[PDB]
Image (cartoon, rainbow, N blue to C red; front, side, top):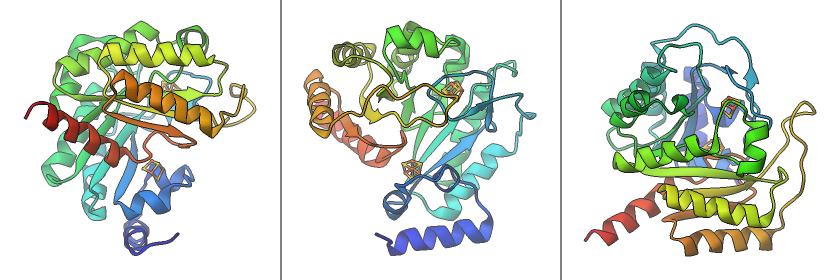
Length: 278
Ligand code: SF4
Ligand code: SF4
């Protein structure tokens, strides 16, 4: 499963000491994604100011804002010659602007140096603050993603810093700004199949274009227990359900990480968007 483009990329990463989520989180898709020249980057440090029971990011006091991070990310993207880059980060309630500047500047830096690279920006909610969100939207990523992750009943318990309505509102906000929007559902957290169906419906109504539906992998014993393993035939049904609701791009199964096939999904959302308005 090891190809020449994966090989070139790992060489470049090693020699330059570039940090990627792909290597550092031990993602099993790396062979496939790097062959398509797609990679994922973490900004804002690895200590989040919030706590979600499914999430592998540690909660802690974040280090000082590193304003050189955007340049650093854009340079890694350039060095790797990526066709698609995902930028993700933690919540930054310690910062007065929630880290809005950092997210936007990273996108702007990437696009200034990599005009042919599609950029996907996965954001926290910024408290749903219109002016923070507007700052981020203006950066103009190819995809604005904000993952609701689970259904309302479970959401209110294991994402105490968020609300289901505010998050859906982030997606609606991004859709009005003209962005292609994306969200993720994590199955195996205790949700019912019916709750999954209404959540997909909610996301579609919120204006979401791309949805990924994946299996919960419990990070450690301190984290939320796995409530089930979804069968393949069940992922297929959910995927067909989402396609039938009119999502432009749908991916379901053991995806391990939310950025799996991000480039292909964007392409489908862009192709269908062009098709519609032609
Ligand atoms: S999901 Fe986001 S806000 Fe919640 S712990 Fe993980 S990084 Fe922090
Ligand atoms: S799925 Fe995401 S984290 Fe994993 S290799 Fe692909 S781009 Fe990197």
